[PDB]
Amino acid sequence: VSAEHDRMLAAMILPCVVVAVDLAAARVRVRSGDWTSGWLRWHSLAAGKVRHWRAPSIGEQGVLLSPSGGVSMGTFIPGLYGDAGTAPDNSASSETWRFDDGASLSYDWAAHRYRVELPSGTVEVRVGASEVRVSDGAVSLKAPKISLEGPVEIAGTLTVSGDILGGGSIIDTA
Amino acid sequence: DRMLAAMILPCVVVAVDLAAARVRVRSGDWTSGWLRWHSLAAGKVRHWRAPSIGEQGVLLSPSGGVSMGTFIPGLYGDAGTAPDNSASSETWRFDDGASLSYDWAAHRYRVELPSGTVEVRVGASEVRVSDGAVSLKAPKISLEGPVEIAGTLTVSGDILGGGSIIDT
Amino acid sequence: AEHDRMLAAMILPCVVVAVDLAAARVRVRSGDWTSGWLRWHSLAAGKVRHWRAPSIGEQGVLLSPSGGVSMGTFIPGLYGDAGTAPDNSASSETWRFDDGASLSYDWAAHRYRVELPSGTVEVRVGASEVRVSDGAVSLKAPKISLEGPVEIAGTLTVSGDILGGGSIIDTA
Ligand SMILES: [Ca+2]
Ligand SMILES: [Cl-]
Ligand SMILES: [Cl-]
Image 1 (cartoon, rainbow over the protein chains, first blue to last red):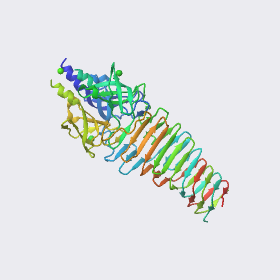
Image 2 (tube, each protein chain N blue to C red):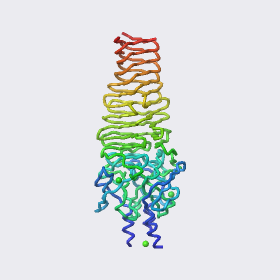
Image 3 (cartoon, rainbow over the protein chains, first blue to last red):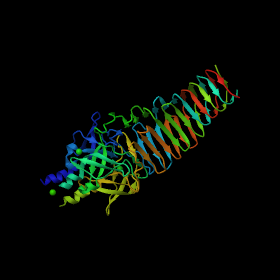
Image 4 (tube, rainbow over the protein chains, first blue to last red):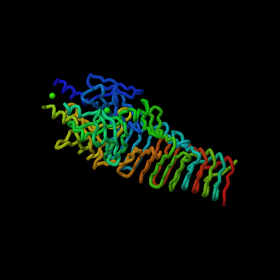
């Protein structure tokens, strides 16, 4: 049982790649060499009062950690850049999520900029019955009350279904 | 031998020290001392999210030295189940029902709070979304494009139009 | 006997001492030893990818299969002098940046807060944009729709025509 020592040793920490995802069960199968695992858990960003979900992709690289080389109970740590998921940025001053559809969410502390960028689609901020929606063709604000505090300038036309009440002058140009 | 076994341990969070940023964990019948966990970031940018009681993870201890082991959380279980099952979305879900998610099939970023508030603040400017209101506040508010209001419009100051102003 | 050195080498406490941004690699130090250029575990490397380079002085652990440290991988995120715990709440999830910016959700207060001391927040979808900066909030789109009673605390300037479906009433 001395070869078992180096066996367990070698099996404790394994470089591996995702080959299968059981989404409903939240498990992955990984491959290290010509060995394929059973259904194993991956470490997510949070699994408590807060939970995060981001299933590892097939082809994603990481490391499997198995207590005493008990590989049937190993857990997977993804996030190794590779052909299935390359480094999405190269800046010393940025924290960036990039998605397959070209979307990205990034903070840059050199430029002091938070950027939510979608080539197409919708960004939605909803709290109860209130909503800010940014889409390809519109920005919409919906609420029981819409309050604009400050000088407002409209570069365009304005159409109002209900009454318009002004506390000052109302002056046209035509 | 014993080092071998002690180097990588399956464990569950059993106590949290918020001020010290440490947790105690349990593996089998063994309970650890106060240990650090690996956060998402600990450099120029830092992230904070304390592991919860009952949160499962792994303890890594160099040369079996469990007194200095570090904890990697995030294993789904009773204290925190997988909050989604989609292959095309990335989701934060919170205990109060709030969620922040991006879906790359639908091309949608969604920030959803059942109740409460979302605040985007830059210097003195703010966009605030709450149960009863959306409010914009800034030294200058600029709307570029044709504006349509389904409702009434009340303006405290003057209304100055560059064209005609017509009622019905 | 030779297994001891290997065991010891499999899991190492370490600190970043060099960063190669272009190659996405780090050199770490443990004891008197400095690694070659090694990979770190990012938050995501699949269809979804995340980027956040470990900082010099950031502490973590190196994992090396069979003690082969030349192929070791780095797990960062151990709070230390190069980056301390940025919060202490049991009810928050928080990013805190070096310029004082923060993004945080608090589930006791039911609040999502994006806070920048200065700079810009930009939400861009196609050609539409909501932008918040020190001196302005701007909405830009082929169409801007406000659904609900709108109250303006200030003056209103409109370059184009104004059409009202009810009364238009001034003070003067
Ligand atoms: Ca032996
Ligand atoms: Cl246990
Ligand atoms: Cl790399």
